[PDB]
Amino acid sequence: MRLLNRHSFVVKRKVSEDGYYNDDGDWVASQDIVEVNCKGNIQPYIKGSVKNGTQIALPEGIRLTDTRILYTTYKLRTSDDVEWNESDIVMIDGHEYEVFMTMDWSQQLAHTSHYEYIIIRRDKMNAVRNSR
Amino acid sequence: MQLETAELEKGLVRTLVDVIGHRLARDKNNRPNVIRAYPSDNSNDKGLKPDQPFITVYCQDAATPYGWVLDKFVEDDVVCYRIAFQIPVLITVNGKGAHSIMLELKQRLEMSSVRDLILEETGATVLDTGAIPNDYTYLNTDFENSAPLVVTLVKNSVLKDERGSIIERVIVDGELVYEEGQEPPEYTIHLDVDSK
Image (cartoon, rainbow over all chains, first blue to last red; front, side, top):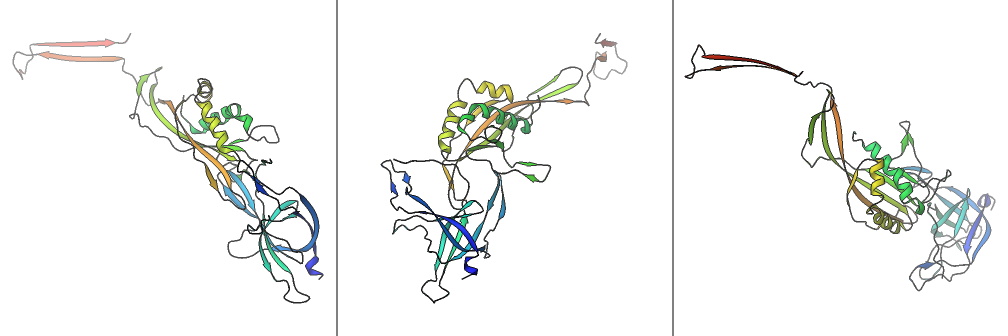
């Protein structure tokens, strides 16, 4: 419906699910990454000690943590060790948001079936590769 | 030389840029990311977390396990004191491969060189160097690898006592007696000695 499609964002799904552990023990993420276009709705998540755009003071400097809730009809998936697949990524404001939680309301009713996700801004860190 | 941790931290920060600057990230000015802990300016401004990997320098405290006063002397008419101090410092690496960088930093502080540069800048000697743990803290989303280390330093500080003064003239009086308490003394000796 109209309100469920107010926002348009990009989603990076690792289509391949062939991640494995090297002969040295390091983790190697699935190789084939694919970009997609999706539509949904993004709002701040107000609950308990959740931190939306909260500035954090540390001895090392300053951080910024954010988290949101997303309503959409697209089936995004989080990490699953039994099915052996990794989570998706959602691009908001040019930054990455990793899908951490999911709530399956699909197949409940005709016109109001949807999904809910809690997406957390990814922390800043340097990059390293282990590919075999 | 006076002991001030604000200067020891600055000297260590300047030395580390050359000693271990090749393994660290670099900012917009091309300078390696080494900073003092709890950055702030103008009494309320707060610094941002640099790009990893980087280093943080934080002075813990200062103690005087070697007595209380080492020397008392006169340098110029002003009196002087010398005191021995010990200063443990904490250096941490944040990022990926923090242990691999702290190991090389350890292996360089023990060289005959580097220890001369530290004394050239801060005017202090390295006394000890503790072990390196391999820590992981969750933060949010992903863990962060860290590797703290403790480097103890030793320095002598000198201060000027502006209230002091020196003796340059002495006046002495004496007596001689056959028996204790002889009220009229047998002889009296009066002496006066000037510095000049």
